[PDB]
Image 1 (cartoon, rainbow, N blue to C red):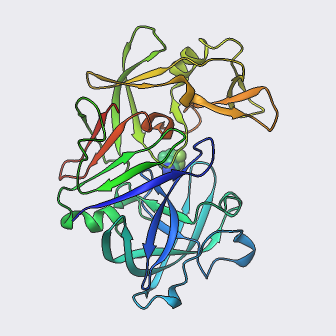
Image 2: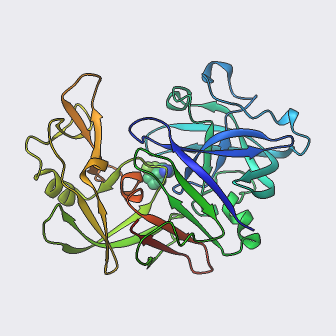
Length: 330
Ligand SMILES: NCC[C@@H]1CCCC1(F)F
């Protein structure tokens, strides 16, 4: 089998991407944030505290003839931005882009933190990291990809995120028309539960490439590119007036600037992020200070190749017995 679904930016900045997902019988379509950095499929639901729902579409398990309570199971997750959610668990039929999994754990939120409530465009998350990170207790549950894997034509999914435009998540096949040149594959460590890999270096603009190993994760659920402070300082030093602002929470730059590109290495290959992809717009409405799309990972404990990086590439998440990542230009 295969599946193919379009993923759409939630706003004009590409702050996140939503993909329609069919849950239950008859189908209830919710728009989920596909997150290769986590491993829970959770949704706003008829069980979510009413004051914490503000415009989201909810899953109502009582209206699904295929829903079954997963008796005794609970879940609770916290993310790197400090947001969180928790609740109980149903199994149900879940389809993405024509690919159907029966018996998928659908984690129904009883509580969500304020940042989820305040984002009316995201109805939940669909985790695509390794199932070892799934938070369901006392019986850990498998991701949608892990459940689908054996049925897929090939044990892979691909992320093709757009810059200020829709893109595609495919399951089970590699669309050879969706990228240019060849795909360069690179080793993955699953020791932390992530799609963790080692970039071979970077360049700023037209500058010379610096060969240096940068361990990090491919994370569709993180907006920006988070890299070591040395690398990030070298980038922003090429932008007149850019500075790190503690009050804002990262590097800002004059909105009048033209940003240089940023290149990262994948083995001997190179992925070029155009400068415009690094512009996250005014820090507040009407400000002439703009927020940068490359930020330091110093406070995080891990480097994160988030959407800013991934949207410059066609990315293969290869879930074979030994997982690997592939990157192509597009
Ligand atoms: N997108 C899931 C959240 C990520 C995983 C590693 C660091 C982080 F919390 F930011």
